Amino acid sequence: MRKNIVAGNWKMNKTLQEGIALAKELNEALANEKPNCDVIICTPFIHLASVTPLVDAAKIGVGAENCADKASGAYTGEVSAEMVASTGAKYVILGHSERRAYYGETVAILEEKVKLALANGLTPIFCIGEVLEEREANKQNEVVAAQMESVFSLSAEDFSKIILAYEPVWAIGTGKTASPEQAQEIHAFIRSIVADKYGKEIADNTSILYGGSCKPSNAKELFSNPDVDGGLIGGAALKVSDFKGIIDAFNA
Amino acid sequence: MRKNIVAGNWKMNKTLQEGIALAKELNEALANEKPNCDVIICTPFIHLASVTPLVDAAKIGVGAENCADKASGAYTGEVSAEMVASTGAKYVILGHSERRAYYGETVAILEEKVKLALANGLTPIFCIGEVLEEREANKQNEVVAAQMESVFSLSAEDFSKIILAYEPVWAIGTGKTASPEQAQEIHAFIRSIVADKYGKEIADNTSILYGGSCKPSNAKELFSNPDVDGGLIGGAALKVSDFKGIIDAFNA
Image (cartoon, chains in turn yellow, orange):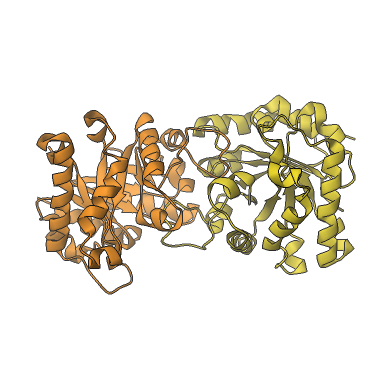
């Protein structure tokens, strides 16, 4: 059955000590219940080895926010998929809109990063999404379809190992908001192109997370949509009560 | 007095466990002597917090291999200078030839990264160097002078806090080698442009490390040059006996 998932993307926030304390605080806050979803914290590279021993692995997984497009070697400053896996992390965000925008990540580079993540037993959280000019031109479907080429070269077995996350990049800094109806529409389209590629069973087993603004006050309405399987959380990931309030949206 | 320094750049090598074991092995190998130089290990981001407690801080410092061009925030995958400092690391490599070549690092980006490193108490190891086509055209001096603009916007007080490293990028994969005489020539030129900017005292206090191929068999000849103050070590950084053999070149 398709997994519901709440994954926090800490982005470039938290010193070593703050990230350790945040992970401890989140673990304490979830101690008295079994969340009705998978929960993941995606941290900067510096925290991974320090936070994996601090969280109940039956409730909280750990992810990196990126990995390199090579397995190892003369790539000063880069951190490989094998390195990420060696910390105990089981997930990696790939293709985040900030890396596409600022760091030149292309379809080909992301295709290689996904392969390396899978070769090291990591679950990619593969991000897609269109910018304001694309949304205003009604090009969102063709944009996300083109971005999915990084993962549609995978075999069916390999594709079944990945999570997708949709980012309405057009809603950043513009005052705009993707309504729950708009989120459902594009999530349904994404699932349909997965089905076109691999058939309905693979598509129906893919978790497609909403990566726009997600807060305790809007999470239940977003997640109640049939094609929205949880969230890749930004700002609310950095405050325990807000992150837990989103996790609570899946309570039975 | 100007510092002699042997700094190892691990590049994108070593799982978490391998880097911990390598740091322990190096610490054990240096236990019975006080090296006659500063010694630094520059590791991937994943190791920093795990390796700083394992090395004798009076003998071995720890560095990162890069840091972000922003202080904090919505830069998924990037690790900030503040994050690096919070691990106990005191150094950061900036401007390595691999990042200039592969990751689009410009004069302006590197100027900002150096400022952020200094704002967080880190000592930059700022790398410069020309490629084969530039060396064959005898343009090495103008190339390194242009690259130094990222740091010549610093005040004299701030510039005094940085280390330089010269990379003969033209010697990678071409069968070529920068002779000790060639290393001395370009190191002397680099020191002369530091003197042109800040005066002779600041220039005479700047450590300028050789970043080409450095092994136990060539380290004494390289380091005996008056303008070569040690090395930024590549392959030999990953084997204790080789790294120690380079450190031994400074023995009295």
